[PDB]
Image: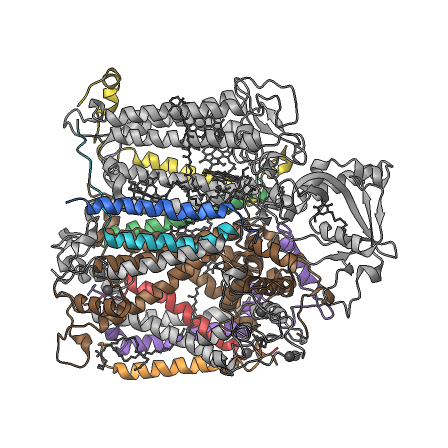
Chain colours: B brown, C yellow, D red, F cyan, H green, I orange, J blue, L purple
Amino acid sequence: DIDGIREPVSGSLLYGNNIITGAVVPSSNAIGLHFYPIWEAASLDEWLYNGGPYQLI
Amino acid sequence: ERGWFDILDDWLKRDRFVFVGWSGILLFPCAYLALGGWLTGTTFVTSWYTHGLASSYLEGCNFLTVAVSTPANSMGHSLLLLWGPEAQGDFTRWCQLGGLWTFIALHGAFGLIGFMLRQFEIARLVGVRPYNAIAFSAPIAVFVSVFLIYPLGQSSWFFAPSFGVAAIFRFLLFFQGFHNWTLNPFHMMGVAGVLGGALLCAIHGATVENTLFQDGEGASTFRAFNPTQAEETYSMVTANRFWSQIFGIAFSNKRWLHFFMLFVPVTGLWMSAIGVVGLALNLRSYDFISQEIRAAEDPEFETFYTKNLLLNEGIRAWMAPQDQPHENFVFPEEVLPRGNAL
Amino acid sequence: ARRTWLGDILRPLNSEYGKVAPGWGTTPLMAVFMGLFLVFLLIILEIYNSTLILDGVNVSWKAL
Amino acid sequence: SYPIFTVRWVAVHTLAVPTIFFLGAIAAMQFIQR
Amino acid sequence: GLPWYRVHTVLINDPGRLIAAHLMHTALVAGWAGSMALYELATFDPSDPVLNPMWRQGMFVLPFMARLGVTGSWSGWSITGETGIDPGFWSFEGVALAHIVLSGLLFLAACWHWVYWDLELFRDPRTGEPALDLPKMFGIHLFLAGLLCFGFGAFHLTGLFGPGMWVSDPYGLTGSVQPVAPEWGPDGFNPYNPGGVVAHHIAAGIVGIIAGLFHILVRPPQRLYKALRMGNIETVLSSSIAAVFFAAFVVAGTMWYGSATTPIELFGPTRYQWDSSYFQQEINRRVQASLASGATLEEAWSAIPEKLAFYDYIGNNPAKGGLFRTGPMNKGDGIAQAWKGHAVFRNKEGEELFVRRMPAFFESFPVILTDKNGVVKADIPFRRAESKYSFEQQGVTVSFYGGELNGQTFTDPPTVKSYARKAIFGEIFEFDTETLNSDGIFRTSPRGWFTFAHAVFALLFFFGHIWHGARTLFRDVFSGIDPELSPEQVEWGFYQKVGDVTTR
Amino acid sequence: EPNPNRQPVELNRTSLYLGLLLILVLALLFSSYFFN
Amino acid sequence: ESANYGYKFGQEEETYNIVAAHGYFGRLIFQYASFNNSRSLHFFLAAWPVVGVWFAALGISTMAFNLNGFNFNHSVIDAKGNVINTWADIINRANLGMEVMHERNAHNFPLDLA
Amino acid sequence: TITPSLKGFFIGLLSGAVVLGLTFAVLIAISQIDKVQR
Amino acid sequence: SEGGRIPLWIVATVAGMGVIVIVGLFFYGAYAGLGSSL
Amino acid sequence: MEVNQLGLIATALFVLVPSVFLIILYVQTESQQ
Amino acid sequence: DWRVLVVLLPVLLAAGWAVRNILPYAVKQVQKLL
Amino acid sequence: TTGERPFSDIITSVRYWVIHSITIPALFIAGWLFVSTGLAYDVFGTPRPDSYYAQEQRSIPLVTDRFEAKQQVETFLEQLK
Amino acid sequence: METITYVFIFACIIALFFFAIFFREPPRIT
Ligand code: CLA
Ligand code: CLA
Ligand code: CLA
Ligand code: CLA
Ligand code: CLA
Ligand SMILES: CCCCCCCCCCCCCCCC(=O)OC[C@H](COP(=O)(O)OC[C@@H](O)CO)OC(=O)CCCCCCCCCCCCCCC
Ligand SMILES: CC1=C(/C=C/C(C)=C/C=C/C(C)=C/C=C/C=C(C)/C=C/C=C(C)/C=C/C2=C(C)CCCC2(C)C)C(C)(C)CCC1
Ligand SMILES: CC1=C(/C=C/C(C)=C/C=C/C(C)=C/C=C/C=C(C)/C=C/C=C(C)/C=C/C2=C(C)CCCC2(C)C)C(C)(C)CCC1
Ligand SMILES: CCCCCCCS[C@@H]1O[C@H](CO)[C@@H](O)[C@H](O)[C@H]1O
Ligand code: OEX
Ligand SMILES: [Ca+2]
Ligand SMILES: [Cl-]
Ligand SMILES: [Cl-]
Ligand SMILES: [Fe+2]
Ligand SMILES: [Mg+2]
């Protein structure tokens, strides 16, 4: 959910992307500039929905 | 056999401040006319009758917004010769009809031919290999494909790039909105060639400058070089170790290094040229069909590819009526694609 | 090398390697034909381009 | 000693002369009012 | 050893094996022509030259056979719709077969010339070294080409002894292979006069014969020989490549703009016919003619041939495809089945409205309806909340005349809007999208692909010309510059004339 | 008789690496468009 | 053979003639536009793209604080006050397309202020 | 018939010939005057 | 007459100042009259 | 995803034919004395 | 058109003046090369 | 060196400046006049600020025919009263 | 299938990095 409007954008190959369209998607607009490490999430599923991998990377 | 041809040859190849050569006969007038044409046009000539645009200093444009604009779409691919059936020898009308655009593009084409011929000619006189000319084939491919072939594939010269800073920016944005040119693997190869070339330029220059031998006492290291010296001025061995250890691999062969510096940007430009030749026919890399099938059926499926298409659709609808005045597009507000609020 | 019947027949056709006419030879003549050719090309180009428009020459599918 | 009128002289002036003329023109344009 | 990119240079001083390599190349190309023809014949549907002609089916070599008079299959059909025809041996299959057999023969000949490379013929009589007299070879080959050119024009194209060529009416309705008389006046240089093609091959043929004799009999001037390095076969490579990219640009252009040698029934319509509404104008002219003769609207439009209507549709525009949208046009919008008839849109006041047609530039286009004066009268709104011109507000209806929907009128907004959406593409057709599993996305025609391939190859061959010309003129420094290059030869003023040591 | 024009061909290891990198990267680039 | 074999890694002597390259390039343009000094040449090769890309980076970094590109939208006006379009205005039309379509569901208020 | 554009064609042709002709006339004249020493 | 009399630094300075004047004039022109948006 | 199935073989050959070319050239280079 | 002579007159007085100053050296150069 | 007088030699000579302190301002003034007399407008066919539109018109005088383009422009220019 | 293809090509490239770095032709000073 890059823009924080509960409209998830698919970035990975397994979820329908090729090399050209694929991406690691920026963390959610609801997060803004907040620091969002894995341990700030209630679960990995949450962390992934909100685009945590982007910040880690 | 010292006839007039050989005497003329003598004179043309004199060692003067500006070398002329046989090639100069083609090069200097055409280059001068293309340049002078652009300066004249951008200073004094309008695009009112062809585009509905002011485009000259005289009209109040600045360096970023002046242009020599393409002719009206109704001119087709007319050569727009001054003595041609459209201008009929009238300089003023010719200017108003966009004759300067073909003037500049054509004298420019032959000027480029002249410059490459000059590279060959001087190479041959001095005794070096003609790799500079060969490398110059890439700018010529770019020019020819973008300014000649591309509009020749389209309806008219109108859709060629106009000769101006902002005019070219428009050309870029147009290619995104209509051609999805960023998606084109040929453009992508061009980008790799250009950024990779800039990269090589920087890394080679920097490497040389930071592996210099101390061949002098001064803190300014520039003085410690003599053009006729036999020795290398920097350490290839140290350079090689540094890069092997920093980055894993390194050049070890200087000739290959400099050949590679020729090869990368030249090849990139040639690839981009091929892509534009495709766009001449609207043979675009516009879509991924699998993406469209999935997205058409599945309204929760979204990628950066579909997002970008929405952007292109915006570009087309919002810029087409003013950018293509001859089409007389009347797009009522209600048909304009817009997201919420904006 | 190896001789053949066909090879012996053709031998004269490949026997004047490097033979030239002195000096400029027929170059002026050549230059004249090249000039003519350039004008010819110019003509068919400008006809195709509708820069040159001739009576009875309608550059269109509606020619026939 | 040196010649005055050379290929370089010509090359310099074919660029220089119009350049000054144009700079005058553009300078004048700065005072045009709509 | 040789770098990988130089492996073929072993042929430069080996005329026999050069000939073998050329033979092998020729065998490969003939083999490709044969195989390609067979594949096309295996996939071609001859059953509807009206709505499923060859250019809809991705046929590339079929039109080139058809162009010069091969129009029939041994199986009894012809591309013009006749059945029960006997094409003789020179059917499509016959041509393909002939090319395959030629390929085999050339292959065998290539082996022979590879093995028996050391023929006396290839040695200079005086020196015993390999040598080709390129000036005389050029004369010989140019003479042959002149003969062939002349014979092609005088016998084949005229039908004097041969079939002629594909000719058609200006709207590509009634095309067939016909004998063509040469046009000897200025209209011979009109690209749309086929008579000009004939005249060209006769005249250029004769000129080629004369010039051939000349190049056989008259040696090169010493100065041109030196200047062009005529003793070096690579000079011939350089200039031949130049001639070839010249030719390639020309055929790309005539394929894209159209000419007598690129008929729309063989390669499809041009983009410019859509740009200028070329077919729409003829359609309207015919309909107006019928109305003027007292016919009803339905009669006027029903009299329009489906073939004509089908030309007036943007899905046949070669500028509507994509680089990676592969295959025949049928794979996109489908296999055309029938003209639905001409859609006439009216608003509640009974004004006729006209859909704004899609320009070739646009992947997508809004649906906008104007009156005859160009005033916007209806549209399909994006934002509904301040819509003023919706079909629902304006009471837009569509009536069809001619085609399968002749006499019908639809009034429900969704249907009317469907038809308006189709109407931006021009005339509306029923398509079979199931058979090929068509995806609904436009593909370009063989005109498009031919043009693309050849512009690209022309452009790359320019580089070939530059490379080999450079190699020819700079052979002496190919491996590097003189180790003993005197600094004063390259420094300024030392010589009066650059690179001329006699001018110090 | 043996042809005197025959030459040995070479491809060094660095050229193999460069070439392989070229082919694999080109494939990585074009594959999306081939699958489309 | 490949010309590359003419250079051997670690050899002390230069593998090309900079004087010949200079003679050539100097004649291509004019003598004083060509580098005879390899150090100053290679410095130039380093400096140009590095400085350029520094400016590119600074562009992104300062537009990060919304000091944006030149705006000449409706800069040219005729005697009556009619807007005379320039290429800047066409650019603006394209920009408007991008602006109104991007993140189509994310804005509730009329100005996109970040 | 001489169309206006055919006339225009001949004018362009003659213009070119005059330009090239003057150029080479001047070039040959200068080349003859200012010879190289050998 | 004889080359070298007027010191090159003075020439450079005067030239530079001329350039500054003319470009200054153009930037002034961005805010006045045509192209000023007013 | 409804990709074009020929993509697979198109990619495979695209990788394999030239790679193999290089490999042949390289190995016979190494086996030369 | 008076504006044509009005615009050309400065350039003509310029060319004429430079000719005034440079004529003896120019004749010296033409004499020397001949 | 290629024989021509060094530029530093020339541009610091008094004679150079005697000549060019005249020829340069003269050219500048000629360009200035070329605009200020309005001659540039007429030469290149560029609209003056009051000549882009007729008083009430807001439509562009766009050229729409190839061979009648000249006549079209002349007509547009006539229509400016 | 596409995914497998993409990832495979990618994996080959990483392998190539490995060999190009650790099993390179040693540069040898002469
Ligand atoms: C010197 C190199 C050079 C070259 C290669 C070009 C090339 C061009 N010029 Mg440029 N030009 C030049 C110098 C050059 N110019 C100079 C010095 C000037 C200032 C005078 C100009 C001023 C100029 C203008 C104002 C225009 C051009 C235009 C053109 C284009 C069309 C030219 C054409 O059709 O000529 C055709 C003529 C020839 C090719 C001459 C060939 C001569 C043959 C070989 C000999 C036979 C002639 C025969 C004896 C004559 C018989 C006449 C009889 C039938 C009555 C072409 C790109 C036009 C353009 O760009 O429109 C877009 C245009 O309007 N040029
Ligand atoms: C006597 C009667 C006669 C007649 C009726 C014809 C008729 C014709 N000739 Mg033939 N010809 C004749 C005698 C005749 N010829 C003789 C005696 C010779 C000498 C052997 C020729 C040599 C000749 C040549 C070389 C060509 C013709 C062509 C033609 C065709 C011209 C129409 C066309 O489509 O042009 C289309 C082609 C052009 C208008 C030429 C384009 C020139 C290009 C623009 C030059 C620049 C190319 C440039 C490098 C491209 C890159 C730039 C670009 C990418 C932007 C027409 C069929 C042309 C043709 O075959 O067309 C298919 C052609 O190229 N003729
Ligand atoms: C032996 C006789 C022969 C005959 C009768 C045919 C007949 C045919 N061939 Mg086949 N072909 C042959 C040999 C032959 N071929 C050989 C030896 C090869 C291997 C090179 C081929 C490879 C081949 C391919 C790849 C294709 C064909 C195709 C065809 C069909 C279309 C021909 C066409 O459009 O040409 C067009 C040819 C030209 C336009 C040639 C013009 C040559 C240029 C203009 C000459 C310029 C240089 C010249 C020297 C200039 C000097 C001229 C002078 C007079 C001034 C037709 C059935 C097409 C087909 O339909 O396949 C099924 C096709 O795609 N052929
Ligand atoms: C002149 C060349 C040419 C042209 C114009 C055509 C045209 C056509 N072919 Mg034919 N064909 C050809 C040669 C050609 N063919 C050859 C040589 C073969 C044998 C392989 C075939 C075998 C063939 C088959 C089996 C089929 C066709 C079909 C078709 C039709 C559909 C084309 C399509 O979808 O392309 C798609 C085009 C692309 C996807 C573009 C590819 C671009 C490449 C990948 C660029 C490569 C990049 C490169 C690696 C970069 C290097 C960089 C490096 C140098 C640094 C079309 C009419 C189809 C048809 O409809 O038949 C009825 C069909 O099934 N063709
Ligand atoms: C008539 C056409 C023609 C012919 C006969 C030649 C012949 C030659 N070229 Mg030239 N060249 C040409 C056109 C031609 N070239 C074109 C159009 C270009 C621009 C792309 C070049 C650019 C070029 C360069 C840069 C070089 C040569 C070199 C050579 C020489 C060695 C070639 C070799 O060993 O490759 C061996 C090639 C391989 C082992 C594999 C190549 C695979 C290619 C890249 C892709 C596959 C293509 C496919 C099989 C067929 C597609 C055909 C297409 C036309 C449809 C040989 C004399 C070399 C040379 O001068 O040596 C001293 C050299 O360095 N050529
Ligand atoms: C002093 C101005 C600094 C400007 C920014 C930095 C430029 C130099 C750094 C480039 C980095 C490249 C990578 C290392 C490259 C590298 O190794 O450099 C090496 C090169 C030579 O080094 P030396 O040791 O001989 O000299 C540096 C010190 O040791 C002092 O002697 O250094 C220089 O030439 C410094 C020049 C300073 C003066 C430069 C002025 C440039 C400004 C010109 C105006 C530009 C304005 C553009 C506006 C559009
Ligand atoms: C077109 C034409 C022609 C031609 C003309 C000409 C040839 C012209 C020229 C012209 C010219 C030749 C002009 C010039 C101009 C210039 C200018 C206008 C300049 C400006 C500059 C400036 C402004 C500067 C700036 C700067 C920079 C850039 C950087 C550094 C800093 C500074 C600031 C200094 C003829 C007649 C043949 C024919 C018709 C058409
Ligand atoms: C021996 C013999 C025989 C047989 C023969 C045969 C059987 C043949 C076949 C042949 C063939 C069957 C051939 C084929 C060929 C083919 C080819 C040669 C192809 C090529 C292709 C290409 C080259 C392509 C390329 C590409 C691609 C792939 C992609 C896209 C791009 C391009 C297009 C580039 C007979 C009995 C007759 C008799 C005598 C003996
Ligand atoms: C609700 C739809 C009623 C009107 C029918 C749609 C316009 S026409 C329709 O268009 C399809 C392409 O989308 C074709 O595949 C099909 O053959 C054709 O019937
Ligand atoms: O997030 Mn991504 O993009 Ca920077 O503006 Mn606001 O926010 Mn969104 O809208 Mn526009
Ligand atoms: Ca006012
Ligand atoms: Cl977005
Ligand atoms: Cl908001
Ligand atoms: Fe270097
Ligand atoms: Mg102002």
Residue B95 pos. (x, y %) = 55, 59
Rendered view: G37 above or below C14: below
Rendered view: A51 above or below L63: below
Name which residue lies at 68% across and 68% down. L53
In the image, J29 versus D5, the foreground residue is J29
In the image, B268 versus H15, the foreground residue is B268
- Rendering quarter of residue L2: bottom left
Residue B149 pos. (x, y %) = 49, 50
Residue L39 pos. (x, y %) = 55, 69
**Does the rendering let one see residue B147?**
no
Looking at the image, residue M27 sits to the left or right of residue B96; the answer is: left
Looking at the image, residue E133 sits to the left or right of residue B284; the answer is: left
In the image, G97 versus E28, the foreground residue is E28
**Does the rendering let one see residue E158?**
yes
Rendered view: M22 above or below B23: below
Q: Can you say which quadrant of the picture contains the C terminus of chain A?
A: bottom left
Q: Can you say which quadrant of the picture contains the N terminus of chain A?
A: bottom right
